[PDB]
Length: 288
Ligand SMILES: OC[C@@H](O)COc1cccc2ccccc12
Image (cartoon, rainbow, N blue to C red; front, side, top):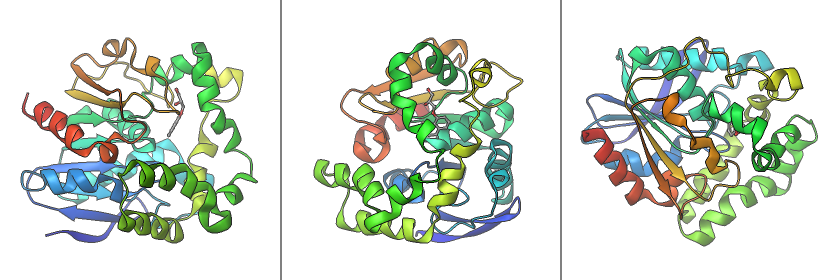
């Protein structure tokens, strides 16, 4: 029942996984993954939703436009908007992780009419993310790798030696912990062969979180609204190196109507680390 194909939106062709029929469940991955990370969710909800897992511009088989400007939050947000539309929908249930959550969160605040329900995994909340980057010394040690992703020299660390950098970041842990199969691993290797690490990096080269005058602002990306009122669910890997727990502190002020599930065991990418647990929390949330 699973299809893979393209969609023209916003001046690009995005590759996307598709399965099932009905109301739209849209999954947004992040760095350095792709549509595949959502495999377990697609298998699970596709008899109740039309599950669509998208390859963010630059990633895997999606077009890879040139210039930092092609990877501005405004652009990416519009990408998402055009996708719900062009898939035949005026709204969806939006499931987000990492960079996809940065985009997703922003989209949701900006277009609450387009999101019936938001499910968010480890990744930046527009408001708290900024707060912890100011107050949380642990979050700054944690986010230090971002200062680093700005340098040209970085991409070679990642691609060099058959993607040594990326394999040890993502493949090694998951193979030894048991959540990556040998086919999952071929899947990833191909995605990095087929996508561009340059464009992957370009997402960060637009981040305005570096100058002291950059850190002053309230929201990670610009936002008129400071409250999101749709039903939201956080599913959170408590042991994630890149995001400190304080990120979820006082979050209800910015999302009244939120539910939060913390996996003390799981790390950055709960969705494929502990699929059955993540899946049951999702079910429960979807029916509340
Ligand atoms: O607390 C804030 C930090 O997480 C900042 O990190 C990020 C900012 C914007 C996009 C991001 C995407 C993926 C991971 C981290 C991101």
